[PDB]
Length: 234
Length: 234
Image 1 (cartoon, rainbow over the protein chains, first blue to last red):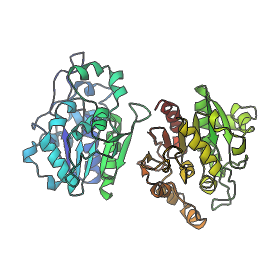
Image 2 (cartoon, one colour):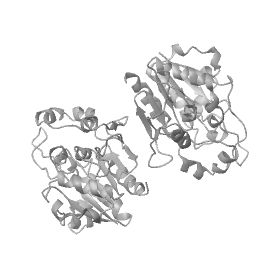
Image 3 (cartoon, each protein chain N blue to C red):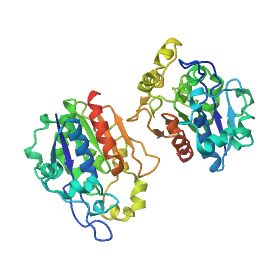
Image 4 (cartoon, rainbow over the protein chains, first blue to last red):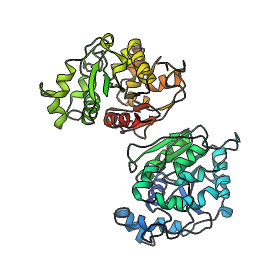
């Protein structure tokens, strides 16, 4: 039982305070934990084989408790597994039942153009696997094609993900535009998907549409992962 | 700017302990409170113009705090309003912006056959209003037609509601099958709707799809009510 957990490979100054974005820690850690818990093996992968942390996700409010302990302890299973991060080439899609895309605002940079990752994702979905994504993770659906129908994998599907209002509240809406980036809600519209919004931009909100699982934000990582395992039976 | 809050008129012995089903207290109270807070007026209506509370919704685990105080206080707005509850005949569909269907298992008995109420809701909706339902409330979607399309109102839409698994867990799926009642998932399947389920059958889980709003269970009453209001601009 393997699970391929994708991470953004973009890590550069993003926020107006000079803080650089990248992988949202708990969006990788909670799914990882949830996966390892049920008895799945986790293989991390990134577009370039490299990654960095979204500095904002390192703040006390987003990283604390056992999470921080596992983060700081280099011998943690999480860290030992992350050290074995793979590049697309080094991956055999046929080895995974679940494809989970963790996020962070960085995914908005490489995920849409990560074709190799999309081919892999598409294959796992073809073999009856489950494709899941949280936060800005659905960004990788931009171009993801269903091999069986030839149509965009999200066309006619109900998904969720980071909200447009959330961007405004974070005050990063100025930047997304400045950097010519599309929001999850934009991507959902562009490819015929039905975007379902949570009551609040920070709520734990996730959706299961057959074998396609999506979550809204960091607070939905766990739920997304849990849904992702359950979805295997669909 | 008013709300039509439909209640189940069924109030007979249900549970395998002699208890009776009917209106689940908070499913009518929280929605009422939310709508009242936002300035909307509220009118209660049932098939018979009468109703009874579901015996199991009266325990401390479901009825407590201010809710319980507003339930026992005869001079409470919630109660003074319930006294003026009207019948379909007394209703003018054009006087409402939202149609909210509170539940309790009792709804499986009357909502599906309450044609007059369906019309009111099809009408309100026809005028660009909002149609919302929580828990077993979606049973009212059984045969509910979109005045403008001719097609079933929930056809092609995404909804959620009380889960089939929940029924088993409560050990009432026997009663249902016996009394020849249909579940929400059934009604969704029957009219071409895409049923989206919560991770846990008890989760506060709701969905907003255009102007069709749905919630899963008592825990979802509030969110479903909030989703209604926000929906009005969709």
